[PDB]
Image (cartoon, rainbow over all chains, first blue to last red):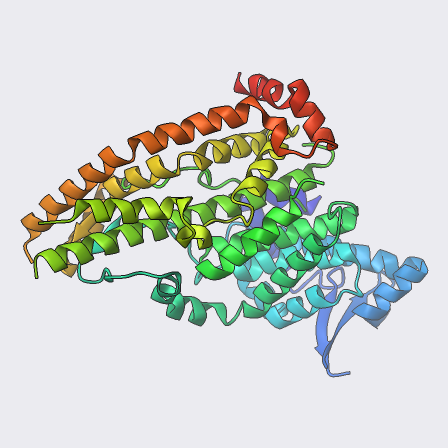
Length: 408
Length: 67
């Protein structure tokens, strides 16, 4: 009831959220709240709770899970209470509620939640609860910020004569590596879980596993959108993502339409499976946007090389041939392609997703299907939108003008 | 380097590329139309999705969702 109270219409309400955070986290009413700690016992997670009779009890999380599996009522009830507590905590931290986020981060660290997530002996739903808590408390915070897959502002001298996928990654690899150190273990766990899910047939067969994979896919989508995945890792992950959707505590908060082309100037019964498929589709759309960015960079590099060579007459035919090479006719761009079958797997997945009952999933599938065959037109339009600046001061002027115009 | 010359060359290359790739875009759209014509061919014959596509499930769903 409290968890539903904090959030209304899937959007966090600041006032009631603040009141609930103050009341639950107040020094009083600590008996109701379960306490989680780490003990050397390497380290293990232990839960200590104060019973309504004022008799304190302590037990390891693994012991509680084993007892619940054996069918003991007390441990199962304690675990369910802990899950509802975790859901309430996650609702408290929704929409970057710093007041409660700070205290909850002090109470629960990244390592503890990662250990709980990676402890498969614990129940699947409990692991999903820790996945949700990790996504909201830690991954979504002040240091993390959204990224733009396509940048229409380029600097003439910074543009390399030749660009490669390795160079494209290395462009931002320093920042990505320095920011990914905290969540590197989480990324590895997510990748391992996705590989395990895709390896098994009929991945969406167990409801608890369905919830866990939905949480994992949400975490992966968040991390990708904050820019914590390199381009190469994204191309490696897209194959697995297509494999999962290969033909054989839920909040539906929607951000800016994922299925939107870059621009220079700006309740189903099985709804869990449909939502994870939709998240996978959003990830695939983001990957396609990064591919478009790489193609634009390649075109810009070719143009700059030709201009510098000609002007220390331009061979437009060679430029046209090079720009045609990327579109997938040749094997040079086979790396860019997100499918190993030449797009047959992607097209089949889109067709199998287009007739699903869920409406947002069908809309996304149709938009992706239409975007698939417009690679050339989209690339040309994106290149036309691109602007080149030879001075860094010009870049700063463009940035300030863009900010002012967007705000106005 | 000259900014005006760079801009002029950028416009020239953009125009040349735009003129060059129109028939390829038209061919891609035609291939999309052809694929939409026979959606089942992509799927395996024994698959139920193939049967639905052959009977018009895909196109019927598209028509229903368009409105």
